[PDB]
Length: 539
Image (tube, rainbow, N blue to C red; front, side, top):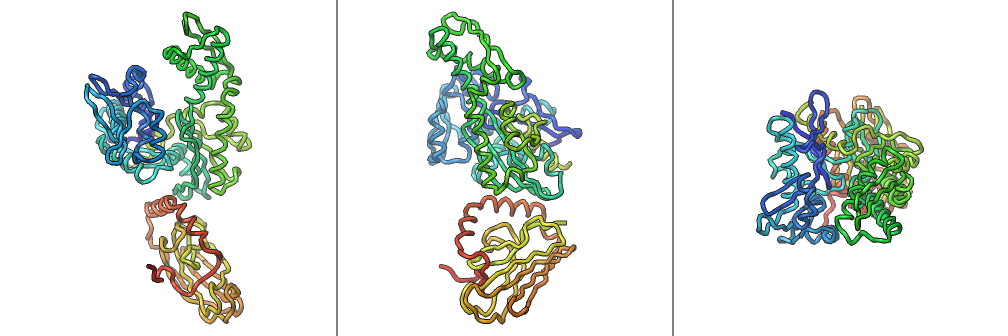
């Protein structure tokens, strides 16, 4: 029946379905609402999920994880070459593509990243089918906002290989926002910050939501930071405590270290709801029982640099988004590590007491939003686009920002690009791109009769006026003579579709850097030439 949402996560994945007016996150065959994204190959079998993760220490070279770090990349990508150094499994280059290479039933086999991820998705699919008692075909799968076209397409292929029809690939932060219904809040646009701290990765995203349209303003984070690091601080703390008390270093013994790590992970979880946790390990090393405890404050101190460090990407995202912290309407906590009270406090204090949206299980929120969107996709007055004119060099100079309420009037003053320019061409464009080449021309007209003056002297006042019915009147006035000309541009056609708008916004995002570079290339901001830049011959 219904399509499922799937958070295909770096360490674990989660699947959910919107039914009977409610999202249900679906437990797997061991009763777990999240499934490790792990695939293991053995002499006899292929394990996926919990079974895979549980045996990793017995079969590490054959147990694959972190495929999401490879997916859609090229073997010689610096990220891949750096990541490979920390993985026990082999990654090899097949005609430029990374493949993970393993031993399976006594033979060497290799898989593309999207094949591995497809195996994880097959597991989630089957989990969903067990729960629903029917075949699951359609799905929405989520990816990090920073994923490029290659990574998105490879994630989609992973879905296709698994027998899923992927209705849409959507951004994790967007999923999170949908989960909290921040898109249904419609009113003036809202700036949302998604703070996603998982086991292995930390992503910060700033979105602006206007009229149901999500725009990613900025992304930042740390691809190497998560709960495991916090666990690791406690582990090392306790190794040192043991060495200090018993004069033995247990690091030599792998299993002892494993047992310690497990205990610290549990303790860390306890410290989110209690101010202390007890560690009890029988015969940790050399027959010595380790029974001790740790306070929340001590855990916080052990982590202080890591925790306080999470604010740095928040700050950078705010800068890149050209927003003051006070301009953030909604803060969303995603990822298990946001359960940590110090993290929540650090963040709330940074935001001056502002309340965080935490109520949805932070491990499940992305899947939740995905499930909602899947449901919608299986079924379940303001300006649509920025409006501006061409200025010298073909650059788009915006008079009215997308999603401005109408009626509206906006005026800006422009000048001439060259000496003794007799006229200016007023070329009215609509779109989110920096260069008019990439936007849509709605109309054009000339203001002639400009008295000869040095470049930059004449003052031409341009006015964009939109009435309640959305009819756009654009006029230019020579401020020295009062002479004027204008054009009327007819819009309400039902000519743009919500999808068109999302598309344009997303492309404007994809191209942001190139656009900026080309934007600030031209010296003066308000200069108008006498010709259409995009009709001018180039090589």
